[PDB]
Image (cartoon, rainbow, N blue to C red):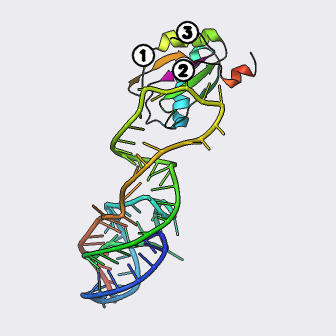
Amino acid sequence: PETRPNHTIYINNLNEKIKKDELKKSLHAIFSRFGQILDILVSRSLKMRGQAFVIFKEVSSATNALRSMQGFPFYDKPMRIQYAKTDSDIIAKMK
RNA sequence: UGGCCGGCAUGGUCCCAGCCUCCUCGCUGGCGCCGGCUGGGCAACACCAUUGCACUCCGGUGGUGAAUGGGAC
């Protein structure tokens, strides 16, 4: 069951051998052109590794970034993108 | 040596270079042989497992079971 459009895009299948700080940076490097990015959450834990939440200011940006970067080779692996199941707190604190 | 002990072997103190290492990366650390016990930590590094939807940091195991020569007194 697919997901509905969201301010945040959920990315996975990311190279797990990359340190958190570097990954967030590199991610911003290739995603900031789709629109303002409020934040990028990355965790290296057993349950959260290989994934990331890029939180865009405007849903259109998440949408664009989703369609444009699906399958993009990143750190030797094809990035897999989706909309986040629910809203990130940073977003709730507003809309 | 991370912390502790035994056996053996071994002239000494320096100086240059090279190499070594999870546990004060370096010139007022170390770089003979052998055996036993044992602490911490995944921070880095490695290996294993993981395709996982968060907004609470948080899987496991491994390494020292290491590294040579030369020069002056």
Q: Residue at x 61, y 13 (%)?
A: A6
Residue B30: where, in percent of width, then height?
38, 73
Judged from the image, the secondary structure of the residue bearing numbered disc 3 is helix
> Is A47 in front, or is A35?
A47
State the image quarter where residue A25 is shown: top right
Q: Is residue A60 magenta?
A: no
- The answer to whether residue A12 is magenta is yes
Write down the chain letter for disc 2: A
Q: Residue furthest right?
A: A94
Up-down: is A4 above or below A54? above
Question: Which class describes the residues within 10 Å of circle 3: few (<14), some (14-19), or many (20+)?
Answer: few
Q: Which label sits in the foreground, 2 or 3?
A: 2
Callout 1 environment at 10 Å: few (<14), some (14 to 19), or many (20+)? some
Q: Determine whether label 1 and label 3 are within 8 Å by CB.
A: no
Q: Circle 1 is placed at which residue position?
A: A71
Q: SS class of the residue under badge 1?
A: loop
Residue B7 location, x and y as percent? 29, 87
Residues behind callouts 1 and 2 on a single chain: yes
Residue A50: x and y, percent?
47, 30
| A35 is higher (above) or lower (below) than B4 | above
Task: Give left or right: position of B19 versus A2.
Answer: left
Report how far apart the C-alphas of labels 2 and 3 lie in the structure: 13 Å
Q: State the residue position of label 2.
A: A10
Task: Determine the chain carrying the residue at label 3.
Answer: A
Going from N to C along the chain, the mark reached first, 1 or 2, is 2
Q: CA distance from mark 1 to mark 2?
A: 13 Å
Q: Please give the residue where the numbered disc 3 appears in the rendered image.
A: A64
Marks 2 & 3, CB-CB < 8 Å contact: no
Image: magenta residue range: A1-17
- Identify the residue at image location x=52%, y=34%: A22
What's the amino acid at mark 2?
A: Tyr
